[PDB]
Image: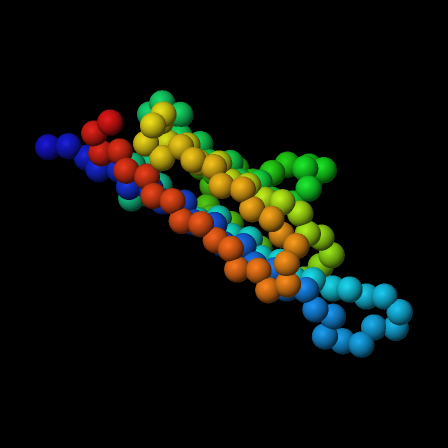
Length: 123
């Protein structure tokens, strides 16, 4: 009689470069979307060795990046002027699903997203 652990990290990134509305001189507006989802209540909500997911997006001049350990999923999509790299690192124990995937945000009509799964029912 043993338990089971199944947690997957899914991050969606999109971007849109287009003015749409005729500007007066210079008004280049772009779009951007970033969401971070994962399991916890299904794959045991208790840590073992490491288990820590840290998301990163946009320039590092920010006050604080994204973190995942005891908080709900994230999802922000709006229009603005930016365009910078974005990488997400996932951890579970040691050699279960510890992986990191880098991405970039600066292309008209971007549709780049990753989905990684992690399973550790025994070890």
